[PDB]
Amino acid sequence: IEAEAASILDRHLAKPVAQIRKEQASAYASLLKRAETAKGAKWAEKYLEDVKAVQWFDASVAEAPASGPKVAA
Amino acid sequence: DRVLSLPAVSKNQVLENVFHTAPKAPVEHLEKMVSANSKVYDALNLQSKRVLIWQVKPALF
Amino acid sequence: LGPQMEALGASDLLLSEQIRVITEHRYTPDRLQYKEGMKLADKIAAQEAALKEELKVIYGDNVDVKHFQASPRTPVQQLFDSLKNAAANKERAAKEAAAAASPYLAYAVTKKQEVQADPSNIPFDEVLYPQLSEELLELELSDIREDEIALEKA
Amino acid sequence: KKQATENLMKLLQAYKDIGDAKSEPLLKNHNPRTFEDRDYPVPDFRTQNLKAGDVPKFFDTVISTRASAAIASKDKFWAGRKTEAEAASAKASAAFPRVAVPEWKKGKTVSIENLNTVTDKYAAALVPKRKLALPVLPEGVKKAVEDFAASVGQ
């Protein structure tokens, strides 16, 4: 895994930044519509529920970054 | 044939051999490293709104 | 003489558009020096866009680039065009540092303006490289001297 | 790539050293007029059997031959200058300052007090190495001379 990640990174560090952001936005958007065209499957609702939970994590960190995410305490 | 006593190299060919490359601006090193260090600020500061510290070292709660 | 009745810098047209009517007059399109003269009119029109853009930030959009191509502004007039926009420059930087995305970028748009609004930081090529700006003067003084030897021989 | 950039920066130091030892002008060797031969035997068109429309095409190929032979003589200067500086590039110092980047340790974070002193190093090279001390009149002395004229009534 160390050798795969060092091989994936060095292939990615040789790209210009405009290529990277649109290679990844193409791969992110293609993988959303594979979960959105999946009609009512339990894995597809759980997929898009976890995309909503990642966006909660990014939003809860933006509210207090020295604290982290907000847990119920 | 007075034109054959003029310098044969044009005024154009002087201005393209003296000004061959468009020179590098003084400010293009600032505004290109600053926009790249603004991504070093974002990911790696602890006061940024998008830090990677909760994505790479998840907190023990 | 026609177009050559007035000097190269002393018409009402811009210098790049005057080189075109001198070259169309002295030479036919067959010639080598018609081709080298219309190419020179592109190198001068390139310098008139770079002078329009440099002075667009001060004198507006109707900059009248003919006046500053013929007689460029002195180091004292570059100063007094710095100072006559500095109040709207220090207030634009303060309105941009307030709405910058992060306190790294907010310091970076004030530190850049703290250097750019000081008129002592304007790079004068004649102050920086004195031997270069005298030799860029003797590129046009030697182009004229070759036209003056051609008239002393005639 | 770091070694290619250190080789190029050592080469451009070798170009600057052996061009300042020879004390040559800056624009002299980039000007292809200075490699032109003015004492060339200048072919006479009255001995070349030209017809009516043929003389301006004769003049163009005497000029463009003599201009190509001045450009190709400039190329022979720089190709001989390159091997002179590449020889001294191999015996050089290679003590260059490094690019100011913000200090980032392995698992640590980046302080904004180090991102800002890096940005100070970018905006301290925006000042020119030799500058006109163009004085702004401060308001501390522009009012001490304005009201001194207003106490007299101007």
Image (spheres, rainbow, N blue to C red):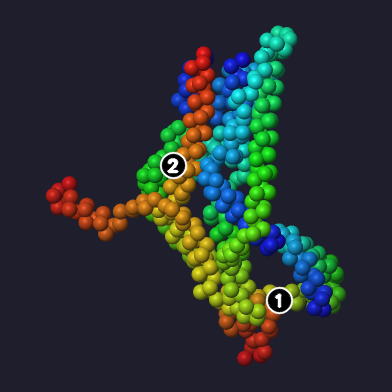
From this view, report whether residue D86 is shown above or below residue C105.
above
Quadrant of the image containing the N terminus of chain B: top right
Judging from the image, what secondary structure is the residue with disc 1 in?
helix
Estimate the x, y position of residue D54 in percent, counting from the top left. 71, 13
Judging from the image, what secondary structure is the residue with disc 2 in?
helix
Estimate the x, y position of residue D13 in percent, counting from the top left. 59, 55
Residue located at (50% from left, 31% from top):
C140
Residue C59, disc:
2
Instruction: Kindly identify which chain the residue marked by label 1 belongs to.
Output: A
User: Label 2 amino acid?
Assistant: Tyr
Q: Nearer the viewer, residue C129 or C64?
A: C129
Report crowding for label 1: few under 14, some 14 to 19, many 20 or more residues within 10 A (C-alpha).
few
From this view, report whether residue D130 is shown above or below residue D29.
below
Report crowding for label 2: few under 14, some 14 to 19, many 20 or more residues within 10 A (C-alpha).
few
From this view, report whether residue C63 is shown above or below residue C152.
below
Along the horizontal axis of the image, is A21 left or right of D144? right
Residue located at (69% from left, 59% from top):
D4
User: Label 1 amino acid?
Assistant: Val
| Residue C38 visible here | no
